[PDB]
Image: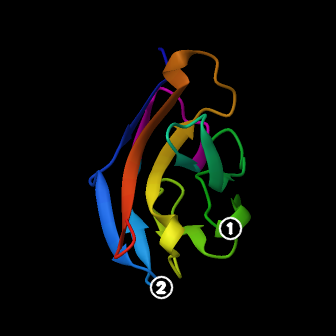
Amino acid sequence: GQSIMTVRTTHTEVEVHAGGTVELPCSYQLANDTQPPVISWLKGASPDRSTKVFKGNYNWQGEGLGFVESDSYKESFGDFLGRASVANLAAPTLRLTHVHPQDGGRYWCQVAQWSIRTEFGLDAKSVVLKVTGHT
């Protein structure tokens, strides 16, 4: 009955050298709701006390039209534009290229129903990024 979101993260922290490429793993399960969710990667202390890194969602196909990676919204923001990507919105690990010294910090993988009807419809977990020689 009740739709329930659960985000998981294999890693609570990842390290890379500045100038390098890093991935921040993220997975989710959405019980009892087959509608595509919306993925946000948010950098900051908390999901609400953050700046946008990435946002995306599969586009609607139909009352049962499997999600299609090519038919999706995907956008990177701000200082991350052109450096941040999510290859698979259903398994929304973030890839960040050309890592800058100040890219160290806390990255929240948030996955939510498009309309968050209840508190059950959103979850988020954070992955720390350590930048070698800077963090």
* Residue 2 in the image: above or below residue 80: above
Badge number at residue 79: 1
From this viewpoint, is residue 96 visible?
no
Is residue 31 shown in magenta? Answer: yes
- Left/right of residue 106 with respect to residue 55 in the rendered view: left
Residue 110, image x, y percentages: 52, 41
Residue 73, image x, y percentages: 72, 58
* Residue 133 in the image: above or below residue 7: below
Direction front: furthest residue: 134
The stretch of residues the image draws in magenta is 28-40
Residue at 57 percent of width and 48 percent of height: 42
Residue type of the residue flagged with mark 2? Gly
Foreground of the two, 105 or 96: 105
N-term-proximal mark, 2 vs 1: 2
Residue type of the residue flagged with mark 1? Asp
Give the residue at mark 2.
19
From this viewpoint, is residue 41 visible?
yes
